Image: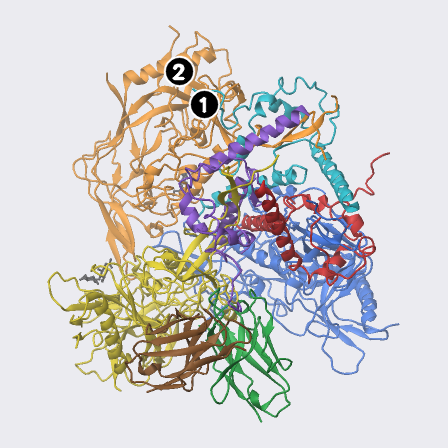
Chain colours: A orange, B yellow, C blue, D cyan, E purple, F red, G brown, H green
Amino acid sequence: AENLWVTVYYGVPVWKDAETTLFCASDAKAYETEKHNVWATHACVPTDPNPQEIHLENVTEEFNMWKNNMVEQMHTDIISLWDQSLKPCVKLTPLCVTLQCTNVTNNITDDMRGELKNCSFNMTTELRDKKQKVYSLFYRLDVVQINSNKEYRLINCNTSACTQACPKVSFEPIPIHYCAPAGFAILKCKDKKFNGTGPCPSVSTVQCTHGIKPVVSTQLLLNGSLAEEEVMIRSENITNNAKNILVQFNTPVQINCTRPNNNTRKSIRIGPGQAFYATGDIIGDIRQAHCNVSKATWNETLGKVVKQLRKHFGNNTIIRFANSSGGDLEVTTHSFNCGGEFFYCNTSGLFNSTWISNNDSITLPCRIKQIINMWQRIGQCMYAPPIQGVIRCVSNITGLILTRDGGSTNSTTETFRPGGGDMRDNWRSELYKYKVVKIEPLGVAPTRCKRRV
Amino acid sequence: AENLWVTVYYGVPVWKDAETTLFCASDAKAYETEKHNVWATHACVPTDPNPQEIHLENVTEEFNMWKNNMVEQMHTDIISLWDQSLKPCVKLTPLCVTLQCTNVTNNITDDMRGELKNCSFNMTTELRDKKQKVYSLFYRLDVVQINSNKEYRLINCNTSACTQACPKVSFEPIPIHYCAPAGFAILKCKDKKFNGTGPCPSVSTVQCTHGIKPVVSTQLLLNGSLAEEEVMIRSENITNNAKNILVQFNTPVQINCTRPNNNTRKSIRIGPGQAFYATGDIIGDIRQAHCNVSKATWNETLGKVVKQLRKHFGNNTIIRFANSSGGDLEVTTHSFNCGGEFFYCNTSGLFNSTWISNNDSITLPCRIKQIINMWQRIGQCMYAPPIQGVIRCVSNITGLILTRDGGSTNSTTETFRPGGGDMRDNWRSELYKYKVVKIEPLGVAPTRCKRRV
Amino acid sequence: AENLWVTVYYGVPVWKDAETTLFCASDAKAYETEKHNVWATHACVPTDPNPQEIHLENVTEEFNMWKNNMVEQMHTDIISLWDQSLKPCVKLTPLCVTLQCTNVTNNITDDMRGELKNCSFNMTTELRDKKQKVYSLFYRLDVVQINSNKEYRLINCNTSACTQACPKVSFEPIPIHYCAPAGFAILKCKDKKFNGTGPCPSVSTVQCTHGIKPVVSTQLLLNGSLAEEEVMIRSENITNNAKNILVQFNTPVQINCTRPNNNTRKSIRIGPGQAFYATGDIIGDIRQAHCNVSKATWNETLGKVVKQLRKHFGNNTIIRFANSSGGDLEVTTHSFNCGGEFFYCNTSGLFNSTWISNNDSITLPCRIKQIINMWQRIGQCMYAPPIQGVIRCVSNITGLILTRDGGSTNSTTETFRPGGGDMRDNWRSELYKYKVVKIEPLGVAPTRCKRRV
Amino acid sequence: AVGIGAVFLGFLGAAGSTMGAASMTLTVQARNLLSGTVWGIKQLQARVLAVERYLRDQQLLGIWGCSGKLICCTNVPWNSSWSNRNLSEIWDNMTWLQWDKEISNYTQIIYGLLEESQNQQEKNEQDLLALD
Amino acid sequence: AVGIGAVFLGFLGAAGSTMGAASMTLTVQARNLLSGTVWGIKQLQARVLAVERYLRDQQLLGIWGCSGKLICCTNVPWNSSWSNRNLSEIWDNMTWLQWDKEISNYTQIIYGLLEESQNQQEKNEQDLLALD
Amino acid sequence: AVGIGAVFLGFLGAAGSTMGAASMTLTVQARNLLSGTVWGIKQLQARVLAVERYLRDQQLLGIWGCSGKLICCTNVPWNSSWSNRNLSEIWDNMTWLQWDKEISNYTQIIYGLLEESQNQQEKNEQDLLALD
Amino acid sequence: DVVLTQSPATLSVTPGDSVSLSCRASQTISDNLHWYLQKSHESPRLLIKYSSQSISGIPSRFSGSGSGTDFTLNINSVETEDFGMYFCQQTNSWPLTFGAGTKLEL
Amino acid sequence: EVMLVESGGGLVKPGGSLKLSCEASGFSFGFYSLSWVRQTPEKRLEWVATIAGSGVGGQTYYPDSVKGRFTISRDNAKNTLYLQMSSLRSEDTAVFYCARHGEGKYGSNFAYWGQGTTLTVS
Ligand SMILES: *[C@@H]1O[C@H](CO)[C@@H](O[C@@H]2O[C@H](CO)[C@@H](O)[C@H](O)[C@H]2NC(C)=O)[C@H](O)[C@H]1NC(C)=O
Ligand SMILES: *[C@@H]1O[C@H](CO)[C@@H](O[C@@H]2O[C@H](CO)[C@@H](O)[C@H](O)[C@H]2NC(C)=O)[C@H](O)[C@H]1NC(C)=O
């Protein structure tokens, strides 16, 4: 009767929150391209078919993406395999020579500017004695003036000699399925109404995540994981001025970025087996690279998000936008990659409106920089090689990264401003559904049976 | 009675074919030589005495040596520890200077040619300011002319700057006992009549192979694993023209390779702690390095292999030989190592005969090359340093690597031609006895007993 | 009765002597200092509170510290993390330039000599074309003359180009708790009278050692593990002349090492992001660095150790001291580190007395050397950067390392001389209490019970 | 027909369900616990984290009376100071995650109670076997 | 007739022998299954593959009724669609390697049968233990 | 009060005590047997060395009759050529470390005896189970 | 002891011919009979195992037959290298015994 | 390959003692049964002693003409066979061969013979 006895129960469903090292599962279809034409396609794991996305009925679960882990590790190792993909490539040290640069041959109007300088210099050949005198073309955002004549030098020539990039590798995003080890499950919040914090009353357990494409955009998140029904905005304290507003909208916005220079390549020999690809002639005209969005679509999407912003800031609130008042070139701009080349656009024809509670396209004139200091590390840059022909890509703008304007008065307007900042916040638009739990069997419960002898 | 019940059997002799990573077993007697004078003498495992070669009575087993594994892994890691024994050594970058080379001081007959060029150049000392003007000696197979006067440069100075070799290490082959991990056996075919494929009806299980010497010869396999009774030949389709004929003969053939130049060394200081050993004077005369084989032995051995080839191609077949019509210098020649220096001989007084079904020595004029691109990798070469004194070695030719001539007519002759090709097939002359199985216990069989409650 | 049966015993207290890889346990309080300001503060393990030091009653155990292990592994990995903390730092190749050095501006007395030379040279800037002409100051123990005039070069410019040290890291000692892995215990000898060998009748088992400070002194051990009651001396055969006599005393001896030059730093730019820290001006006067010990304390300590030495050499033995007849500069001197700079003192006003069985301070004029070849490796040195301001430290002399004088006559005097020799013998003053055993359960004993069927 | 996907749940299927329905199939959480040059060491460090925390619970299970039986009675009584709950509820009212909070202070006393309750009865089998 | 012929009663010794002589020594293949700076991580990843494939068979054996008995009867009958051979032959005519070919289609049916025949006997043991 | 730290010792507490007092607590040596970029591989090669030498003893334990019972009688008699000692002494006079020196020659004769005494008892159990 | 009687003691044959060597046992050694060749200055060499079983490395011209007490060794085209002393040997009982040998000379 | 190389033969006066050795390599020594067989100056072959292999029982066997006089032993760790002879007779004069048997059921035959060492008792 009352002589209740301890009975243990092994293999019993309970879990605790934890954090351990997860691994890839690259899709097996991306294994056909041979021997790392992109980073991390042979290094980590081939995937599985039909991942067991299984519901967990009558389960509510307090998810989180702000104090969440596993978005720090994915940023950590993606940094790490970016450094893994730069050790084979050729260091570009012997380019720190005193340049001699003139204007490129072009119809120089005073309104437009010479974007590309000539910069004929001296460089060692494969023989150690001789030094050929070679020329190139260079953007104005890569040379500074050494101070008649006009002689420049590289901007990164101060403080950071950095490598070239091998044309075997490619900067494309491939899908990545993160998988838990044995003894760990991955909870996925299936709730169609789920802000940042709060219990998610419809979860489901997987073992491997869906294919995540690791991209790097600061503003205008691209090419991934559209929302279900509405345009959901989610943040930390909405009465904070330091916390970004991760907008994630429902329908995609088509972007049409291009670069109309032909940009012929050529190979200069640095030394023994060290080629260097420099842009030779540009055939045709020197025209500016741009991006396009539909004005009816972009204005309709801002009509959507100005409706959803009033859900948090009340009605009769004169919501307006502005264009990220100041900062460096890498936070005020939509800095991204397209086919292996690095566009810095100018979202100032976009973020410029004001909204009260009552066919053509917008062209964004972008600009390209060849050395690259993503994640703003101290002693690195990255000489991206030139690429042949006209360059054009098409992508889906999926989510924004806004930032409120830190008012302190009893006003109605709210001049929202875009701002990228930390790149982890991109992956919080991908890792907000998923948490990782630790299966903890071997429970214990009293019942009326005793181990007889 | 007929109510037979399942009974599992753990620890039951069954195996499946598999492939996993094997490891060394270096001989413990070779541990006295300090700190890797040969590769893999401190890095991997001291061996065991008396490996348990245990018979497997009433066992036949389908071996294979062409779709066999473990000759790809041994070639893989031997490549890797070859790079491990080159990572400590000194890089030889500052030698890419425009040379100026004349004939060496010698009694120049028009029939012989100058094999060694003088090549006096400039090179920096350990001080960055001073530049000594030093001279050397160089072979004709290492300089090309930059185009009065006559000034050369190194041949590898295009596209591959490559290291010197540290005189601590030695290029001799040491025996290597490959051993399987736990759960894996090594089947050894004990059949005294066993070609490549086919069921071997007399096997025996070991855990560690006998001591394998890793050598590098293209033609004329050396110093290993003579046959038992006959001259054993083995191939793939003998009606194929792309598959080599791995000849393995029974009695060894003694070779007497030498180099009669004295070839005095000297040490030039490259920089801080970077010595470079260059050949100074040669004492005596400039004579050609050669090899000897006994003509009475060689003609009887070709009398053996023309009998065994007629065993596959019938009798009254006029078998003749020729001399490997074309290719590079490392495939048309018997390219090998002797004491740390790289002889390239000329097997064309050898492979020149014809055979119908009815005391002196053969001298092979060899030639030496100092940079080395063994395995023909893309961005490597290998400056072998000079060595003091007259050089002479004695080795046993053990097996050939022939290749038929792809006729398509109803002729009788078969002009065989030697050809090395892939170096893995050398080690298929060592790894044909061994296959690796995975012990798979826990079988299951029905019998008449039931688990009582 | 007599039908005794085997009964196995799992989990049974017995141990054997072994050797396996141990690991760190850094104290968690030293984890606040961010990202390796000293080596191995993020790399290895945060410690535990209250390590389970548990007595082992009725246990005697034959310890030993001379054939002991675990002082070889700690020297091995401390070598290894010393090399781990030098791979990020900048290589100092382009300093091998022909110097031109004069006397520093100072009141040159003929008795003193110019310790610091001027040495203005040429060195390339970050541009490969330009070459700045910079000047420095350098010690006399770092330049030799290339041979009117007087022009020097670096001493290490022969045979060993070696790195700078990054000013983020620091060479200060932090405590290190060595811990055994699972299945291994650490026996600690709690005997208050315990020489090297001999049964220790009071042991205790731990899992983590107390906090060991890795210091680097050759003679005059510092800052660690004072003795319990007496001044205990310990050696191998005390009638041997090759085995050092590790004195370890009970009360600390306060040292007061200083450097009263101001020694202003400056940063010369070698190339792209390669700074080089050279000592600029010296503010004030050029005075010699010294150390102080109390003469009453030092004479009191020799009054202690001449009593304890007579315990091994009998009474009426006229014990005298001398000053380490010969050896290198790093064995004839008290070579140590203080705040990141390397004092070489002169213990010859100290070790000079004689003792028969019947307030002021001693100042030791030290001297500083900037390149450093600790452990006397072949191809390494270590350019320690200069440091700002007056430098002063205070340390406890804890133990000496003496060495007798190998007489062969029937004399009474014993002129002892100090001598460092191997640096491992320092760490045997810290790891003599601890041995590591391996727990081997599953014993077996006969008793009167049988497994019933 | 016979055999439907309604009552045949999956891994962690009854994880919110009551104990009387979670304890019907415990083997499914048991059996999916082991199977299912730098990106190989994350495989290594996922494996060498899995087999120790598998062996540690299989050791705490092993050193009680429960070798691999996965449900086993024991001999210690259930002191109501631990849980104070009714019996008729705690197999169909509460849930297992509510239990692990409801007991988590008193664990490592129960696991500590189990070792003497195994070894005292253990020594009593040997003292029973020694006399005969 | 004196029987002086050498016999190797070692590892894989009876690998060609009949079942009545192979089941005499099964421990010899069992016990030689676990024991026996870049080529040390091939030792690490060979060791944690050896202990992994040891743990996989020790888990599949463990979750059946056979904890460590290494030979154990069960309750499932032997359907003749699997082997259809006589009983009096298959313990002294054939050999184990002939068995693994003779059954390899019918594996993963037996391993699936074993789990329900264990968990059914397991829960019938619990239903027996619950009433008392 | 009741409960003091004097007779409630810790790890290796009775390591000098007699066998009759060391066999009182064997579990304390049992539980401290599993738990407790270059300084991570010394953690890896210490962990997979701990779990290998734990599994090797759990395998040699597994193939005798003693799965995890930690104390078990057997069927082999005690040949006096091994120890030749009295029984009334060897549970309270000598100690376990004195035993391991006093017997270490005769292990692997006993260890070979245990496997055959288990596998013979095993097949005799099967021959008993086969007839019914 | 088992006496093995080999017949003939000596036999001269021309190379290329065939021979039948006799070994007769005093008790049945049914299949316990092995044949060895010992050439001059050499150790004996096994020709035939257990009355009739051929030996790897021994030419196929060596064949054995016989059962019980009466045994025969056939050599079906004798070669020059085959001439020597021929032994039969029994393993039916202790002590191990040999026949007296047939000497085949050229 | 299988090698058995005997040593220790010599000229011995009658009544004396002599230990022969046979050093073996190329096979798992302890598993095989080994024998001494002698060949008399008239070339007759006489089995002299046997010690069984590890899986054969390891007993020793002798014919009556040597029993109580000859002792066959093995040192498996060094792969050596021994024959200790005492109370020697002139009839013991012979070449003594070490021999290795075969394997399994069809292996009680002599499979390998050594070269032999000569003992002369006179
Ligand atoms: C390295 O050189 C670059 C350009 O030569 C420096 O960048 C500018 O330096 C001037 C110095 O007067 C400043 O006024 C500018 O503000 C700098 N540019 C920016 C964008 O801040 C740079 O300061 C130098 N030093 C380092 C450490 O990079
Ligand atoms: C690198 O240069 C070497 C020599 O300067 C080239 O080798 C030869 O180049 C000449 C060109 O005049 C050709 O006629 C020969 O056929 C080349 N040799 C061989 C064996 O083909 C070499 O081609 C250059 N390139 C590389 C990749 O090595």
Q: Which residue lies furthest to the bottom in this view?
A: H122
Ligand 2 in which quarter: bottom left
Q: Do labels 1 and 2 share a chain?
A: no
Characterize the local packing of mark 2: few (<14), some (14-19) or many (20 or more) Cα atoms within 10 angstroms: some
Crowd rating for badge 1 (residues with CA inside 10 Å; few <14, some 14–19, many 20+): few
For the residue with label 2, is its CB less than 8 Å from the closest atom of ligand 1?
no
Question: Disc 2 marks which amino acid?
Answer: Glu
**Disc on res. D3:** 1
Depicted A62 relative to depicted B439: above or below: above
Residue in front for this viewpoint, C250 or B420: B420
Above or below: residue E114 compared with residue C379: above
Which amino acid is tagged 1? Gly
- The residue to which callout 2 is attached is A230
The quadrant in which residue H21 appears is bottom right
User: Which chain contains the residue that carries disc 1?
Assistant: D
Quarter of the image for residue A5 reads top right
State which quadrant residue A374 falls in. top left
Q: Which residue does the image show at 17% across and 72% down from the upper left?
A: B320
Residue C225 location (% of width, % of height): 73, 55
Give the CA separation, mark 1 to mark 2.
40 Å
The numbered dot on residue D22 is none
Q: Can residue C23 be seen in this view?
A: no
Q: In the rendered structure, the residue with mark 2 lies on which chain?
A: A
Q: Left or right of A106: which side holds B185?
A: right
The residue mark sitting in front, 1 or 2, is 1
Where residue A232 appears, as percent x and y from the top left, is: 42, 18
Dot 2 falls on a residue whose secondary structure is: loop
> F126 or F6: which is nearer to us?
F126
Where's residue C83, x and y in %?
53, 56
- Tell me whether the residue at label 1 lies in contact with that at label 2, contact meaning CB atoms closer than 8 angstroms: no
